[PDB]
Image (cartoon, rainbow, N blue to C red):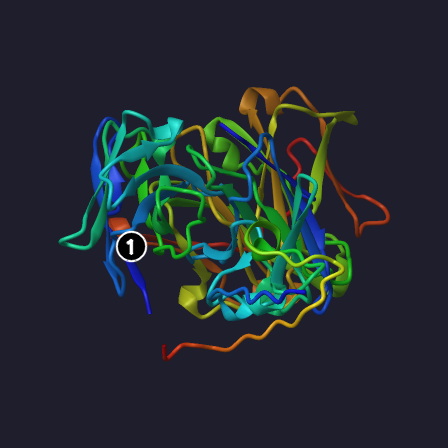
Amino acid sequence: EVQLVESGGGLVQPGGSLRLSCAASGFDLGGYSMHWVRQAPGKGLEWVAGIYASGGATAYADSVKGRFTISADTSKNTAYLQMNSLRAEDTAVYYCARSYYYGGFGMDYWGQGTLVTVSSASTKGPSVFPLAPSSKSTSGGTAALGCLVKDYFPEPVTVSWNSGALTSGVHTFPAVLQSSGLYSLSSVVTVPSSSLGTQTYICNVNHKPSNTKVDKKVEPKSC
Amino acid sequence: DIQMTQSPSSLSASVGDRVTITCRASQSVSSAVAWYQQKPGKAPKLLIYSASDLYSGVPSRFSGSRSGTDFTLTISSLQPEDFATYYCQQSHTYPITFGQGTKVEIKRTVAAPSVFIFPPSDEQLKSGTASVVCLLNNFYPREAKVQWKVDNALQSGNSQESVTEQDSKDSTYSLSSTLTLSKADYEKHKVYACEVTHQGLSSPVTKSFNRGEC
Amino acid sequence: TNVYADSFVIRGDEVRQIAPGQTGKIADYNYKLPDDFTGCVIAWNSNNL
């Protein structure tokens, strides 16, 4: 068994910095290059940098050149990434990975990734707006109530209904970033339509990083 | 700066079926291409290195070959755990460049969404803005879009869309499209409509409202 | 006329490449036998050595 354990993620203001670490266990660093890979939310992987543990030499991606610096320590058996002058453009999950020699070999084993976020709005709690059900005939006789969870930062926000009691028929979207620099997501509950006036339908949006939540009751509108 | 072109953008194949994905480097990268699988909430895992060498811990189902300059990843027989977006990277020289990712879908029976529309309400309009919301629920396949109309004309440049994750059993998903208008723009038009279209819909679903209605 | 005993140490999944008419990392860049090859290939796990 080989392990790569990431740490050091968090929230950074534009122009700030963050030092990330990745510990190795079950293997040495020497003879291998340690690499960092960036994954912006909603995107694929981007190379950041690599260091040959038995070299001390490094190489960097153009996308992070100058701004990011890497190193490795074979006594501690750990890899590091120093990210300076961070921008909103740098929001991503930061992964550590290993490969043999300086190059020509793919990254075999990866750590799990630590999220680092940057925005013009350092933080905001969510607010929630309703979505009315259709009052017209529908296929299957079903209908749904919903809401929009708006203007919060950072992501994740977990959404469930009726204080976690209603998971059945629950459909939520991942958040996307708005022009406000803040995130928003939609959600609904689909049930036989007569249930929309019987069951409780409260959007419960949970955001642990700011110790907050919004409990929003959604009910049919007359229309 | 060698880029990775991939095709198809997505592939539909059922469990037990064969999947092929092609990665095309813009320049010579020798045989240093590597393939990855990633699950939501998890690290990427190496499947194949040095073009055709199987990585430890990876099932034999993942194999591949080169012909001329074209390299293909093959899943000999799909299992429920082999549905992921697969990525290529080139390790030959630096910088390492990654491709966009090819999504493999379960090829479930294709069908239309349950569609709902919510016209901007009087309460929502208190913000000084208007937002028209149209939702397509529990449908399949992954490819869908909404064409918006105003006064029966096509709209463009004033809409946004978001898409959710696929269901753990049926791989269905929902799509949500919106229009953004200032209250002042909302006031300039009378009829709004959501035209739903995708592979499983034989007749596009049109939902509509008059300004001020619900 | 002659017999040649060629030898090397490989991975288990690579024993399948030591044959004429083959492709793969060894078959293409490390060791080949001709399509009209006359000979026998013997291989044995040496993990304890």
Residue at (53% x, 30% y) in the render: B2
Q: Is residue B142 visible to the viewer in this orientation of the structure?
A: no
The residue sitting at the bottom extreme is C48
Question: In x, y percent, where is residue A49?
Answer: 33, 37
Q: Residue furthest right?
A: B202
- Tell me where residue B25 sits by quadrant: top right
Q: Secondary structure at mark 1?
A: helix
State left or right for residue A114 relative to residue B127: left
Residue A99 lies, in percent from the top left, at 38, 50
Disc 1: which chain? A
In this picture, is B183 found above or below A156? above
Image quadrant where one finds the N terminus of chain C: bottom right
Density class for disc 1 (Cα within 10 Å; few <14, some 14-19, many ≥20) is few
How far from the left and from the top, in percent, is residue A142?
Answer: 69, 62
**Residue closer to the observer: A173 or A83:** A83
Q: Which residue is mark 1?
A: A208
